Image (tube, rainbow, N blue to C red; front, side):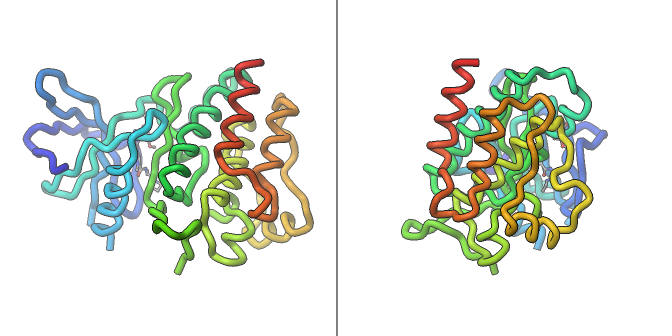
Length: 262
Ligand SMILES: COc1cc(Nc2nccc(-c3cc(C(=O)N[C@@H](C)CN4CCC4)n(C)n3)n2)cc(OC)c1
């Protein structure tokens, strides 16, 4: 799992940045070829968090999730991942309002397949949103950003926290309980974002105003040009009572069926 720093070449430019530090593009020397990578570099609390993130990614193996190549302990701690060249889905759609409905359905279906896998594997993502889906190509999405993610214990169906409120289900806010069904709620917000071309959800509202709106049974409206069936699926993801909300098996099947007849 530990990579050799001498086999990594970084670019100077940064792709992004935050309290942890920076994300830069680089190249990792393999047997013959070089592999383009995205490298999360700590400008260092922070250590354990990066190590926990890599620990999650190390356990996942699925085409619609960002793969970890390894960790590099060098001038800084570095989490080396396969590169998603086109970057975050929200930003991509904000810059490319031409993308067709059918292409959006294809991408959100790919996210649902990743998430179905994540749910089967008993991990909760806890930060599922359009900014955390990355594009390989205009037709290939991957789930990223496993910093808040939790491996559920073998005999528990949720994680009790001890916040991206606009993406959180009522049971997360009210009871601090995070399940695969909480991620389904998030997935519905992600779908709304995708069909809105990377607009922000609940525009202009405080977290507490969002919670009140939801408790009145109010939900965001159908984005322009979003198909009825896809809005109906969003509303099903925003099922208030977690017990009655679909899991990702049911969500992925709905998307699959709709895509393969649209
Ligand atoms: C071409 O432009 C871009 C390409 C890429 N590609 C690409 N590929 C594979 C992996 C990753 C990647 C980025 C991050 C990350 O930590 N992002 C920070 C800024 C925000 N997170 C929210 C909590 C931390 N992680 C965990 N994985 N990124 C990314 C671009 O981020 C803005 C931009």
